[PDB]
Amino acid sequence: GNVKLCSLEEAQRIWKQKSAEIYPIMDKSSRTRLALIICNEEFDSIPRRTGAEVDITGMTMLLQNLGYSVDVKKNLTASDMTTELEAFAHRPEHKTSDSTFLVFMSHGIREGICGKKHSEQVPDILQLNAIFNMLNTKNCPSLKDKPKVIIIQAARGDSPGVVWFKD
Amino acid sequence: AIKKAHIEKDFIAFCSSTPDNVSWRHPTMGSVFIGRLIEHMQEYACSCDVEEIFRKVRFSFEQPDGRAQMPTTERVTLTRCFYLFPGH
Ligand SMILES: [Cl-]
């Protein structure tokens, strides 16, 4: 991972111009940062998401390089994703971490992220509303006051989101 | 003693729901959204906060030409700037 590192002078150059407007970070020696990647590549009745192996490799490596222990879970149902998110919320390493990253990669629709058993006939969907709920202050007190970065790759099966115009 | 807390605070989501179906030539290609997220994270994690890095990601995707993406930042309840401080 080629993450451009932050120098000490540059770090305090950031710490000065914006004082108490920056989330506090724990010391490098005794912090236990966690990050969770759920990625669906193989599905029951919807097209295989090839080159997701490259997205997993990429994201893990990067998150690792930003100091996160990365779990990686593959090909789950919405019920399985929910359970997995529940487990992640009650991980004790959070109490001694300053933040977290969640990464979801799958097929998307209106409602949200497609599970593996999904079909347009028998829907298997996890909704974004549910991800936030399991990670909020109430249902996850250890991550309270700490930045939670959710990253979602949920391509909708639509026509390209571009248009032509006369110039 | 008891204190009051917001139930939903300190969230930031970054989503690409712009259609991204598999390429015919080289199907084992990595998603460009992810690739671009990674390149900007690698370059700007040291100097910009995430809310900004997500914008920079958008700025780089401003002109459609090949694989066209325009990812949104959603559900932001960040009250402070989140700086990753790489290697600190
Ligand atoms: Cl193609």
Image (spheres, grey):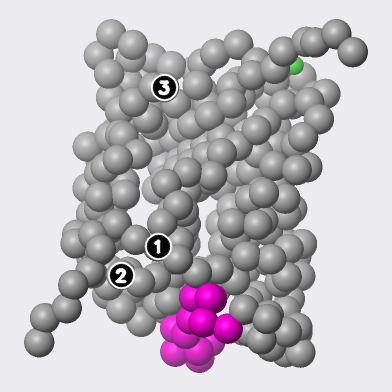
Magenta highlight: main SS: loop
Q: Which mark is residue A109?
A: 3
Quadrant in which residue A80 is drawn = top left
* Residue that lies at the very extreme toward the left in this rendered image: B1
The label shown at residue B10 is 1
| Left or right, residue B43 beside residue A147 | right
Residues at badges 2 and 3 in contact (C-beta under 8 Å)?
A: no
Q: Please give the label number shown on residue A144.
A: 2
Residue B50's spot in the image, x, y percent?
60, 60
Judge by depth and name the residue closer to the eye, A154 or B48. Answer: B48
User: Residue A11, located in which quarter of the rendered image?
Assistant: bottom right
Which label number is shown at residue B42? none
- Please give left or right for residue A59 compared with residue B4 in the image: right
User: Tags 1 and 2 in contact by the CB under 8 Å rule?
Assistant: yes
Q: Percent x, y for residue A152?
A: 49, 41
Marks 2 and 3: which is nearer the front? 2
- Residue extent of the magenta highlight: A19-31
Circle 1 packing at 10 Å, graded few (<14), some (14-19), many (20+), is many
Report in which chain the residue with disc 2 lies.
A
Asked if residue A29 is among those painted magenta in the image, a careful observer would answer yes
What amino acid does circle 3 point to? Ile
For badge 1, the amino acid type reads Asp
| Mark 1 close to ligand 1, CB under 8 Å | no
Residue at image location 27% in from the left, 18% down from the top: A123
